[PDB]
Image 1 (tube, rainbow, N blue to C red):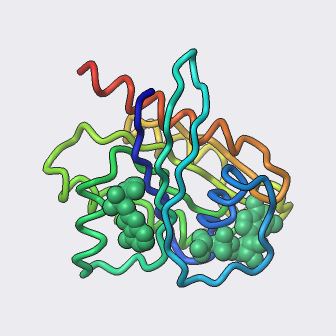
Image 2: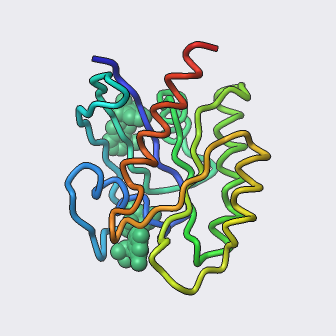
Length: 169
Ligand SMILES: Nc1nc2c(ncn2[C@@H]2O[C@H](COP(=O)(O)OP(=O)(O)O)[C@@H](O)[C@H]2O)c(=O)[nH]1
Ligand SMILES: O=S(=O)(Nc1nc2cccc(Cl)c2s1)c1ccccc1O
Ligand SMILES: [Mg+2]
C-alpha cells in the first residue's frame, strides 16, 4: 500500500469540493458551503498498486495563511483547478503555482492543470490556451466535469502518476 497526499487548489467556485466529493462519495453537490475544508482518505488501485489517497479539499485561498503554508508543505501533489467559463480563475493559476513552488523551494512539484465545468457550453477559456499553459509548466492538462463525472478519476489518478514518477527523479 502506498500513500499519496493530494491537495486541491483553485479560485472559489471552480469546483474543488464538487470534484473531491464526486471522487470519494460518487455524487454531485449543487451548493456546497464554500468555507468547508476537509481531508478525505480512500484506497484505490492504480497501475496495479493499492494506493491510499489522502486528499485535502481546500477552502480559503489566502496568500497569508500559516495553515495553507503547512498543507503545501505536507501535500505531495497539487490539482490546480480553474473553470472553463471563468477566465479570472484561469489567470489565478499562475499565482497558485508560484505559491507552491515557493513553499517547496523546488521546481520539481507534481501538479495537474484541471479545467473543470466542461459540461458548460459557454466556454471562455480555449482548450488550446490551457494546453499551452500546461506545456509551459511541464504538467498534464485534463478537462473534467464534476457534474457528469467526466475524467474525475483520471484527474486524480494522473496526479498520483506524476507523484510516483517524481519519486524516481
Ligand atoms: N455545471 C457544473 N457546475 C459545477 C461543476 N463543478 C462544480 N459546479 C458548481 O459550481 C459551484 C461551485 O462548486 P464548489 O465545488 O462548491 O466550488 P469550490 O469553491 O471550488 O469548492 C457549485 O454550484 C457546483 O454545483 C461542473 O463540473 N459543472
Ligand atoms: O495536513 S494533513 O495531513 N491533514 C489535514 N486535514 C485537514 C482538515 C481540515 C483542514 C485542514 Cl487545513 C486540514 S490538513 C494533509 C495535507 C495535505 C494533503 C492531505 C492531508 O491529509
Ligand atoms: Mg469548496
